[PDB]
Amino acid sequence: KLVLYGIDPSPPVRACLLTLKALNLPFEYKVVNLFAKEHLSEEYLKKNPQHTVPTLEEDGHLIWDSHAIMAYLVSKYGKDDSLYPKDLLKRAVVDQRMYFEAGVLFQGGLRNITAPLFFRNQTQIPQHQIDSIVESYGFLESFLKNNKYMAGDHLTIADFSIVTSVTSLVAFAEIDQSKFPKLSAWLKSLQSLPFYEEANGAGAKQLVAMVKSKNLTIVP
Amino acid sequence: KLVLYGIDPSPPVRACLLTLKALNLPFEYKVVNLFAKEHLSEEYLKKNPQHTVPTLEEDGHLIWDSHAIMAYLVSKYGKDDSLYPKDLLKRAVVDQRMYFEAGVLFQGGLRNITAPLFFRNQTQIPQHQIDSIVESYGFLESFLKNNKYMAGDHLTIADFSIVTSVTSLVAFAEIDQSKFPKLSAWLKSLQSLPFYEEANGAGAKQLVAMVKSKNLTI
Ligand SMILES: N[C@@H](CCC(=O)N[C@@H](CS)C(=O)NCC(=O)O)C(=O)O
Ligand SMILES: N[C@@H](CCC(=O)N[C@@H](CS)C(=O)NCC(=O)O)C(=O)O
């Protein structure tokens, strides 16, 4: 019986949700309230010493990091390899896109703001940070230059990982459709998935709301 | 025919160099000098629109990101899977450690200080960024609780990835051996591979010297 530990404002938890729904997998969900420091409990640290969400539990085994989890799920459960191609050159693109999300989008763009924001009430955001988010939208627009989805011609876990961060980063910088038409189209396409709302949309809305309620300032 | 594009001070370049050497693969090393903005030319942007190093070229096909390159090299060229185990659960640990390196160590620890430093000449490092680095050492210490290497009982590309970052982070935050004994032992187990200096040491030192010449303060 799969168990996912998380809370839905979290982008990587949402990426796992997307992927479990895409694989038509049932699972138990255990909420870990980061705002009440539940991830810092002795019990949770034994599951995941990095004290992050998501964690996946399967027959006693604990796996963390959304990208590891997503790859594991497709590899283990996928009817075929559509969501995570076995072809090594294809896999290298999916992998690259996910490492891009981990580093550039999630740490560099999002957590770089949200950690001081919710922890230290740092409500002033330097323009150079917003510039970096917009630079990353540009990189995503480049990724899509000759492909319908982030890593090629079909939907993969790279799309799921990337969309979770993109739909959070828009709390700080909107995506200019005139600059980033492909990124814009791609997002609407992901938004069309039957499981999109339940896996990503719901949590994204709650995170965007939390951010908006903090009344941020961009400093030139 | 393998070509690696990079510069030695870059940790993810060094991770690829460590892996190439471990697999004993011939390659051409094309220097792309970030300080001369060689990564921003039309030619390089065609290879990698992210304008990062490393980039790997294999018979004309281009791939980038150290972690993706390392997984690709072991998968394609490894005589066996020891450096990147095929077992899904074992792979999941290797994968997680590499994503940790990408986000927490490299972006959150290293590039967080080196971008302001090299782009904005910010030589004053907020004490809390050093703390965060030390916290990351602590996470690495935990990863080593029941295992001699980062992802289990043998050397993997997770070790290569993490060493490159750790050796760069040392430039800002010394490792206290009384707090992180397992990490300290682990780092010696890497510093000892016969190909360590040529693949990681040289460029790690160069980055240290660049960092030192900037005369930092906390
Ligand atoms: N690379 C990890 C990132 C996980 C992460 O940083 N999650 C945040 C929530 S969005 C978290 O658990 N923060 C609490 C903490 O780090 O203490 C993944 O992809 O799962
Ligand atoms: N996730 C990438 C990170 C690559 C990266 O950020 N490399 C730096 C050098 S250490 C770089 O190319 N900086 C130049 C730039 O980003 O413009 C990887 O693992 O290869």
Image (tube, coloured by chain):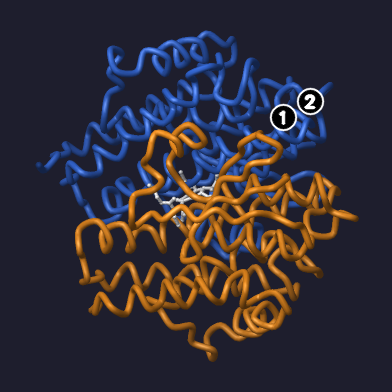
Chain colours: A blue, B orange
Outermost residue to the left: A220
Q: In this view of the protein, which residue sits in the foreground, B40 or A123?
A: B40
Q: Residues within 10 Å of mark 1 (few under 14, many from 20)?
A: many
Residue B218 can be seen, yes or no: no
* Secondary structure under the numbered disc 2 in the rendered image: loop
Amino acid at pointer 2 = Asp
Image coordinates of residue B156 in percent, x first then y, are: 74, 62
Which residue, given by chain and number where applicable, does mark 2 sit on? Answer: A81
Amino acid at pointer 1 = Tyr
Outermost residue to the bottom: B178
Q: Identify the mark at residue A172; answer none if there is no mark.
A: none
Circle 2 marks a residue in which chain?
A: A
Q: At x 55% / y 32%, what residue is drawn?
A: A161
Q: At x 63% / y 62%, what residue is drawn?
A: B17
Cβ–Cβ below 8 Å for labels 2 and 1? yes
Circle 1 marks a residue in which chain?
A: A
Q: At x 55% / y 14%, what residue is drawn?
A: A148
Q: At x 31% / y 57%, what residue is drawn?
A: B115
Image coordinates of residue A187 in percent, x first then y, are: 45, 16
Q: Identify the mark at residue A84; answer none if there is no mark.
A: 1
Residue B181 can be seen, yes or no: yes
